[PDB]
Amino acid sequence: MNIFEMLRIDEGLRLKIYKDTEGYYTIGIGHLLTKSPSLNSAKSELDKAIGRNTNGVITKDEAEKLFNQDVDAAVRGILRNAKLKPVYDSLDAVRRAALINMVFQMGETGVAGFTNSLRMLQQKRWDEAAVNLAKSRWYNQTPNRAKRVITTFRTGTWDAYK
Ligand SMILES: [Cl-]
Ligand SMILES: [Cl-]
């Protein structure tokens, strides 16, 4: 298992514009299009992202292409962030994937806001970090996905995904 296969299980794959768990316009593998309520505005972003007139539909390759761009952006956002970088640097490879997963879903700002959890991860206090991570809107709104990520941080294995 790797970061790509982990995120593919978490986000699924859809080739036509759809609404995410928050109600926003998305396409492919969890690629947010816009927070706007207008479908037209979403179709406009989609064509801009792809470079062709898509009329709301993309192929598998186009989806995988946006996906590779998005994982690359998440990693780099972490390495550029003064709060995330040190945590990232301190973790093993499995746990690193779990941090990337959080960032992909919620953005760097968002993750950076989990001050207490990040400090516990840095300290390698696994059971205490899992407990604090669960006291969030994240966990209450997407509980099965949060539990998978949280178990990954707690154990340091891919069990939750096998
Ligand atoms: Cl883009
Ligand atoms: Cl969920």
Image: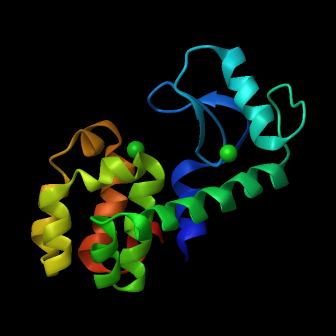
Q: How far from the left and from the top, in percent, is residue 57? A: 82, 33
Image position of 129 with respect to 19: above or below: below
Q: How far from the left and from the top, in percent, is residue 39? A: 67, 16
- The answer to whether 49 appears left or right of 23 in the picture is right
Residue under the point 12% across and 77% down: 125
Q: How far from the left and from the top, in percent, is residue 5? A: 59, 67
The picture quadrant where one finds residue 85 is: bottom left
Q: In this figure, which colouring scheme has been used for the structure?
A: rainbow
The picture quadrant where one finds residue 54 is: top right
Image position of 53 with respect to 136: above or below: above
Image quadrant of ligand 1 equals top right
The answer to whether any part of residue 91 appears in the image is no
Image position of 41 with respect to 65: above or below: above
Image position of 103 with respect to 159: above or below: above
The answer to whether any part of residue 12 appears in the image is yes
Residue under the point 75% across and 25% down: 44
Residue under the point 39% across and 57% down: 102
- The answer to whether 65 appears left or right of 19 in the picture is right
The picture quadrant where one finds residue 41 is: top right
How many marks are shown on the rendered structure?
A: 0
Residue under the point 90% across and 30% down: 53
- Outermost residue, right side: 53
Q: How far from the left and from the top, in percent, is residue 66? A: 71, 52
Quarter that holds the N terminus: bottom right
